[PDB]
Image (tube, coloured by chain):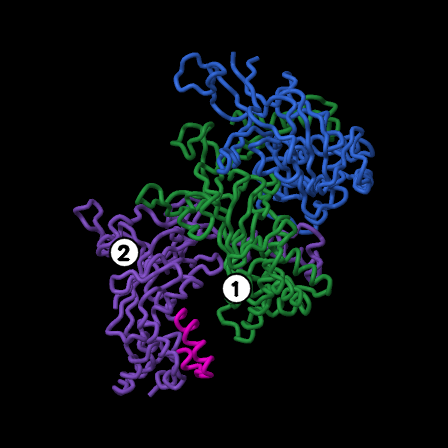
Chain colours: A blue, B green, C purple
Amino acid sequence: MQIEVTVRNITPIFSAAPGSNYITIDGTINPPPGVSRFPLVRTRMMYVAADVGDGVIKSVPLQIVPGNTMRSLLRRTMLKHVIEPALVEKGNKLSIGAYATAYSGNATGNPDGVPSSFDEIATMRAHPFIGLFGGGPRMLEGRLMVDSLYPIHTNAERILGAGYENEMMSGPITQVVWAFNAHEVVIPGLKWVWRISLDRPTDAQVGLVLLALNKMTNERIAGGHSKDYGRFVIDGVSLNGEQVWSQSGITGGEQYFDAVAEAIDGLSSKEFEQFAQSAK
Amino acid sequence: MQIEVTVRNITPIFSAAPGSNYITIDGTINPPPGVSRFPLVRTRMMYVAADVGDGVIKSVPLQIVPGNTMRSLLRRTMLKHVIEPALVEKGNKLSIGAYATAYSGNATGNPDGVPSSFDEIATMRAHPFIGLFGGGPRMLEGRLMVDSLYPIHTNAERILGAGYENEMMSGPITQVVWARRMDPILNLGSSEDVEVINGGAVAANGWIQDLLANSKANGRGLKAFNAHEVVIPGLKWVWRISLDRPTDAQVGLVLLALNKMTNERIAGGHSKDYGRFVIDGVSLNGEQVWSQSGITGGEQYFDAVAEAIDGLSSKEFEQFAQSA
Amino acid sequence: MQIEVTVRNITPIFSAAPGSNYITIDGTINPPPGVSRFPLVRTRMMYVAADVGDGVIKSVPLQIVPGNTMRSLLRRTMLKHVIEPALVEKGNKLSIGAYATAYSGNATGNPDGVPSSFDEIATMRAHPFIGLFGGGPRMLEGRLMVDSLYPIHTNAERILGAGYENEMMSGPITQVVWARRMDPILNLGSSEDVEVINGGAVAANGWIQDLLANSKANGRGLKAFNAHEVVIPGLKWVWRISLDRPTDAQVGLVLLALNKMTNERIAGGHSKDYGRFVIDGVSLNGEQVWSQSGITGGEQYFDAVAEAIDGLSSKEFEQFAQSA
């Protein structure tokens, strides 16, 4: 529900881009001829309309972390940090296909084109995780809408023009790190905006997203696990635009946290098996 | 009555064009076969005669959100934030036919052959919702005509004859954005994560053996890799919502939808946040009425629609949807 | 009088052509059977003879709006905007037969096989509106000859005599535009979305069951997916409005229709705002009489039609519409 966090990276970010790219040296990034080819895995590309040239609007490059990856990040943080640890007691162990439908979108391929009856979608979009992350056999839409990670940049000004007059990154953002094959990463210390959106959500769903954002620092995204890429820290979480973050955590809007705590206290596996069972 | 809604998208716009398109690793949309083509669902495209060079007009591409899509979007935001709160505050109860005819123009797929009597036409066209969006079994014509969503680009230069001669974008506005699936049971690793799965690690290993048996060998497993072409974010579009002899209540309902358009999404791709936008301006027969706090102006239309929410019953929807 | 109305459509032109035409997922029109075959309604296409190799002339389809459609469009913007305000401003009221003879050609689909007397013919052809559009029960010939709306294209090189030798568009002028209608009861989602339908969620559940029944097996569900071929927007068209020995009031009525031609739709695809167009020029037997405010010049025609609407009466429409 218009949840917008800002994060700071400390290590490089490597959200690799699909491309057959190659470099010779830092003077030219993609050479025309094939002398001294050294292959490149680019970071993720986002051409964007921006005010470059003092008045005109042009497509310019800018490097992001995609919202599909952070949607999977928010998903795995909640599933592996409260949903599995508050599911590990009192029985109710997940099915294997239920675990696939919780971690991925579906249990398997070929989702059945038979739709589900409404008493399902009424029960599932009210439950904290399933209505947050829809899909499965019926490809349920869900409520939670995950934006891609936008660096607070001069190319990113028209998207982020309202709340940020200052703290505005300019010039180069990215650099090449070799190890003879080259890799392209985002320089650390950049401030990013990650936007989380939900339509008409229940108290437990926004509490779950909020609880996950209390603890988002631990899991590393968009880089090599061996290469130490992915560390980030969060300052400035906004909840309908009002600042709800400190060093110790959220400390604000406690009705959301009470609601989701009562929800995972009442969490059961039956809704997850009613998700993942492909009614073909 | 002409309304020109000039908007700026916040997120990328993805309104999927039908058509099984294909994409290589680097560019080359729809390659010759055998270069390992990946599936590609492009954004909705519109060919436009445009001034390419001096004296030549060619059918160039320019990719849009369809006018059917935003006609249903304006209709859906009208129903979700004006008509349904009114009908639940007064307790007026729709039928399944009235509900389906309100959101989809018809109740069933078979329209009635007979035409509606003229008193019924006058009542449902003086209705501030049904007059905007007609349909029904007797196939009513709505007063509202919704154009498709044109970006302010050189390609739409012949389209934007009046206004928008500035803010004139030259280069390309689309992007191939890649999204993949994994099988996360192919990413388990530790059996302490598998102790949540009932039956132990043997069932997870059976799913490993299932996907390797699929890999040597048409039941699809998981772990896809797909691309979709989206519009870039941050570019400014124009929308045209015109009206055919409107009552002031119908215009007030359109402006009530335009006040809180920004909650809804002008795209598909719901989970990827695609479709977030902010309205830069709203032109009411050329005059600008848009502010940061909704619409500043058009007070007679709003007053007319405030008198139209009062006196609004479900009965008009019911004999609009009732088939002879 | 010969009138060259150069218009430019702002939105995609869609004048639907008869025929059970079909389309695949891709752009193949009327495929061999066995492939996924969605219904396609195409625009009205006119075969025209043009040079294909520059020395050989063959029949090449050219998208058009019919002269019947453009003629009744002209009649309706001439009648609704000029004739009806002049009748209600002087208090003149037509019968329903004279009303039908005004907008259609007659009141009954049976015309009487009887010649009308010459005084009636002279008064009817000296009448501005009735002289423009004949018909009636005794089948008068009008003075207005309305041709089809031809896009200024290289396919119409033999159609367009001179004056457009540098302003010809080339290439394909059409796009298949896809449309669909989901069942809205499939898209409810929340128990607060079923607080407006009677019976509640379980009643909505019953509808889903019918869809599930319709997933197994003449009623038709709302879920539809289809396509329509449209002419591309931004195309420049040429309209031939010709006049057979006209009075000055008749030409003035045609110029009044083209003057306030702006807020009208070229018929077809009303809900998608498809008929929206602007006029780039009007030639009055070869001289350019169009400005940005409308039609400049032709002053004697405007004074003659202004003197014609004063004294416009019901009784002439009654005796035109009265069957022998």
In the rendered image, residue A123, in percent from the top left (x then y), is placed at 72, 47
> In the image, what residue type sits under mark 1?
Gly
Reading the image, the residue beneath label 1 is B142
Which quarter of the rendered picture does the N terminus of chain A lie within?
Answer: top right
Numbered disc 1: secondary structure: loop
Reading the image, the residue beneath label 2 is C47
Q: Do labels 2 and 1 share a chain?
A: no
Disc number placed over residue A54 in the picture, else none = none
Give the distance between the C-alpha atoms of the residues marked 2 and 1, in whole angstroms: 33 Å
> A80 or A116: nearer the eye?
A80
Tell us which disc is closer to us: 2 or 1.
1
Q: Which residue is drawn at 34% across and 74% down?
A: C303
Queried whether the magenta region covers residue C100, the answer comes back as yes
In the rendered image, residue A262, in percent from the top left (x then y), is placed at 82, 41
> In the image, what residue type sits under mark 2?
Tyr
Q: Main secondary structure of the magenta part?
A: helix
**Residue C214 visible in the snapshot:** no
Using the image, determine if residue B286 lies above or below residue B140: above
Left or right: A200 with respect to C42?
right
Left or right: C243 with respect to A120?
left
**Residue B311 visible in the snapshot:** yes
Give the extent of the magenta segment. C76-101
